[PDB]
Structures are given as structure tokens and as C-alpha cells.
Figure 1 (cartoon, helix red, strand yellow):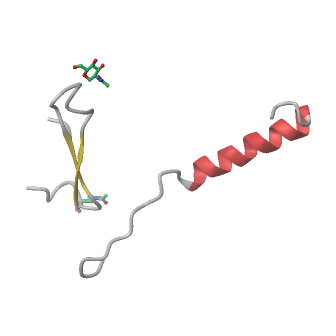
Figure 2: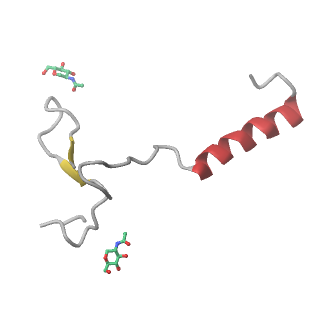
Length: 31
Length: 36
Ligand SMILES: *[C@@H]1O[C@H](CO)[C@@H](O)[C@H](O)[C@H]1NC(C)=O
Ligand SMILES: *[C@@H]1O[C@H](CO)[C@@H](O)[C@H](O)[C@H]1NC(C)=O
């Protein structure tokens, strides 16, 4: 699955993304 | 590791929960019921 982490649109529009139990070398900065 | 089925990990690890119980146990051996 894919989850989106947001501080709330009333604070910022930046976002982080969690790819659940996926090895981070096969996803397609901060990784 | 199946077809559409996944298992999510718990937020507290087992190390964290053992830390919590050792803090409770050191509170009671040493202060009685005053820390609660
Ligand atoms: C939400 O927005 C209102 C007005 O724009 C502001 O007063 C409030 O503090 C905001 N909430 C947060 C959690 O930033
Ligand atoms: C992802 O794959 C690399 C290449 O084999 C491996 O070194 C790494 O340990 C893997 N990720 C995890 C969390 O084990």
C-alpha cells in the first residue's frame, strides 16, 4: 500500500510518502 | 506475502514495552504507591 503523511493543509502543503513493507530500492532527496 | 493480504507492525516495539514494565517495576520497588 501507499500512505501519505501530511501536517495538515492549514499548516503546509508538503507531504511524505510511505511505501509499506517495500524495499526502498524498488520504489519507482530523502529516502 | 500473499494476494492482497498484509500484516502491519505494531507502533510500540517489544523493546519499548519491556522498558515500560521495567519503569513500573522500579517505581514500585523503590517508592511504593506514591509514584502513581
Ligand atoms: C487553521 O487555520 C486558522 C485560520 O486560517 C488558524 O486560526 C488555526 O490556527 C489553524 N489551525 C492550525 C492547527 O494551524
Ligand atoms: C533491499 O535490497 C538490498 C539488495 O539486496 C538489500 O541489501 C537490503 O537489505 C534490502 N532491504 C532490507 C530492508 O533488507
